[PDB]
């Protein structure tokens, strides 16, 4: 496990995010209900949501867009987001929705989750089925609909460990949390894949992670393992969207 050189980067970066969010109520409040329960926001959305909240930015989005549930159904339901006319209510983004809250506060995050989802071409789904998108479309969406013209997608595939971590440290050092994805290899190519935020590191070279499960099993982890409570372990096909900040 490679360690942060303090003559190049900061000696450590303590957990940046203050949100401890997830994919269900009230984050999904504005998504359709179904007979298999209400649609969930998606890991990509929840992770993007959290980072955008960190910067409380942009004030307002750019344009509009719609996706449909079920995904490629010729007559599915419209799930639309008008970024252009939405002034995001950052003030009412509670750090933790596990308690009670005003509706104002519910709608605050419910919209961000919606929009982030829509902006990534989310294929929405139920609690059992899940909602997924592609990190690549997430980048594209951030640029187009959120105004992050520097947002950029990259895979760990194309970088040696030293180079990858250089970016990880330098970005965290600059105070920029990272949207980050990886997949946990299945027993017969039945892979499981997830998106989350990396919001720090320590002298030891471990990383602070916010998985977006209402802050469950959140904490400092090894970037090569990423193994929350030994249920899963996200090693393969790691990737990120950098260039997200004010």
Image (cartoon, grey):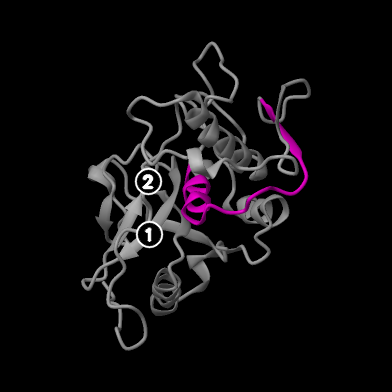
Magenta includes 227?
Answer: no
Does residue 159 appear anywhere in the picture?
A: yes
In the shown orientation, is residue 244 left or right of residue 197? right
When the figure is inspected, residue 197 is found, relative to residue 162, above or below; the finding is above
Residue at image point 71% right, 30% down = 72
Q: Residue 235 at what x, y percent from top left?
A: 37, 56
Taking the spot 50% from the left edge, 60% from the top edge, the residue there is 239
Residues in magenta, as a range: 46-69
Which residue corresponds to mark 1? 199
- Label 1 element class: strand
Q: Position of residue 74 (x, y in %)?
A: 78, 24
Where residue 24 sits: x, y (%)? Answer: 45, 28
Left or right of 166 on screen, residue 224: left
- Residue 27 visible to an observer of this rendering: no
Identify the image quadrant of the N terminus: bottom left
Q: Quadrant of residue 189?
A: top left
Q: Residues within 10 Å of mark 1 (few under 14, many from 20)?
A: many
Q: Which mark is residue 211?
A: 2
């Amino acid at each position: 496990v490679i360690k942060p050189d303090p003559s190049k980067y900061a000696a450590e970066v303590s957990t940046l995010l203050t949100t401890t969010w997830g994919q269900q109520m009230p984050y999904n409040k504005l998504l359709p209900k179904t007979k298999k329960g209400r649609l969930i926001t998606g890991c990509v959305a929840t992770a993007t949501a959290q980072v955008l909240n960190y910067f409380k930015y942009p004030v307002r989005g750019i344009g509009s867009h719609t996706v449909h549930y079920p995904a490629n159904d010729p007559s599915g339901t419209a799930i639309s987001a008008d970024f252009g006319n939405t002034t995001y209510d950052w003030a009412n983004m509670k750090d933790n929705y596990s308690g009670n809250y005003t509706e104002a506060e519910a709608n605050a995050v419910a919209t961000l989750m919606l929009h982030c989802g829509v902006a990534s071409e989310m294929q929405y789904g139920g609690p059992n089925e899940g909602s997924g998108a592609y990190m690549t479309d997430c980048a594209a969406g951030l640029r187009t609909y959120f105004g992050f013209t520097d947002a950029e997608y990259i895979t760990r595939a194309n970088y040696t460990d030293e180079q990858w971590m250089d970016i990880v440290f330098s970005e965290l050092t600059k105070g920029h949390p990272l949207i980050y994805g990886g997949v946990s290899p299945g027993s017969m190519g039945q892979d499981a894949g997830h998106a989350f935020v990396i919001d720090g590191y320590n002298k030891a070279g471990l990383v602070s992670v916010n998985w977006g499960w209402n802050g469950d099993v959140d904490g400092y982890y090894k970037i090569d393992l990423l193994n929350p409570g030994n249920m899963y372990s996200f090693t393969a096909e790691q990737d990120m969207v950098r260039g997200v900040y004010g």
